Amino acid sequence: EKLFTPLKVGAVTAPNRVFMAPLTRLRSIEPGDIPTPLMGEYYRQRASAGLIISEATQISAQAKGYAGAPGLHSPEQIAAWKKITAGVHAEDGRIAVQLWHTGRLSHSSIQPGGQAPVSASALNANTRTSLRDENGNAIRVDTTTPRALELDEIPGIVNDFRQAVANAREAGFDLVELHSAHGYLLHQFLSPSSNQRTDQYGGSVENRARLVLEVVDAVCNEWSADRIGIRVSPIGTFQNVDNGPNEEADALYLIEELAKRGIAYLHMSETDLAGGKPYSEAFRQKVRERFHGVIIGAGAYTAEKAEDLIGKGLIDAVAFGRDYIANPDLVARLQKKAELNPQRPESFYGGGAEGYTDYPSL
Ligand SMILES: Cc1cc2nc3c(=O)[nH]c(=O)nc-3n(C[C@H](O)[C@H](O)[C@H](O)COP(=O)(O)O)c2cc1C
Image 1 (cartoon, rainbow, N blue to C red):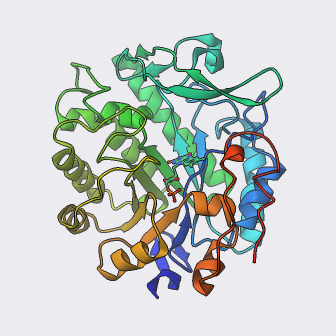
Image 2: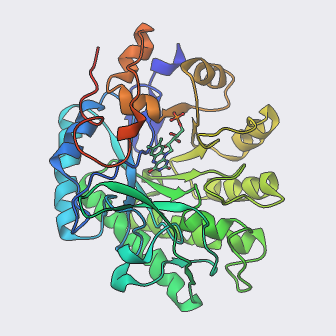
């Protein structure tokens, strides 16, 4: 049973291959987008994971797209995350921070100055984000049409990722995961659907990948390549952002470039919750031969599917999302073949301890 064997993930050694996927839970304090001791307890409960990957976390105030999502840009955010990572370490866990900029998947009412959010191009996401009502409860609101970033603004985006990585290292995270998936800002540049630019950041796949590779380079230089992972969702459609008409070839180009940086891991989000066609074995093989770090697979996995693909040498670890929401001791449950707790989806987003810290261990 390879799932319960160790794995070196860049600078860290995970004791098992059962990872906690990044899960937005929208329970942070406003004003200030501040993580809380409740969040600290939730992560501490899950510290037996081979690796915890945190909820997506803003690199800056401009990055915010969801009310209740935390940041890693302010002194008060850094101080709060320091307590959270210390708690995970006291339980012998390891924790990466997933860092995002939401780009156009946002609303003006939560942006600095109440202005339109930014993106590769001035195209509405045509979906909804989560705000809070006057009682502090989560509500789904249509996205605001973004403004296209000017060329002279792109270095500031890269610097915001760099600074957020400095902050993450200071805050005690073991690794960083760049959120280059699911229709957020980096994916908005990668995708020809959302990126209609005609400068060096749009058009060719090389230009579409330019921003994410500049970010990768900047964060590797700020910390170390063996502390950097990246999440991609490069096959299919995620939150209305497709991967264009040459999605496999474009994915392999990006993966070959990422491999050159010697980063710690590639995390592939294979499907959204509504499902879609499975990755082909041939595509998995093409990814594996191009990337020489850890590959994490995610998206409706079972322990059996994970074991199959680990045993075939195609991936190294699996990230579970909803099963980690509901099972703090998922590792022990999978190892013992125990039943899993029933999930309560109504409390995934927003609220308090109920549906968050009240799922029991075995
Ligand atoms: C409530 C919820 C929140 C999520 N938040 C994030 C997130 O912040 N970042 C991310 O990359 N994926 C996020 N996802 C996707 C999950 O990381 C995971 O890839 C997905 O849940 C599919 O896997 P599963 O079948 O194991 O749940 C979220 C999923 C759910 C259900």
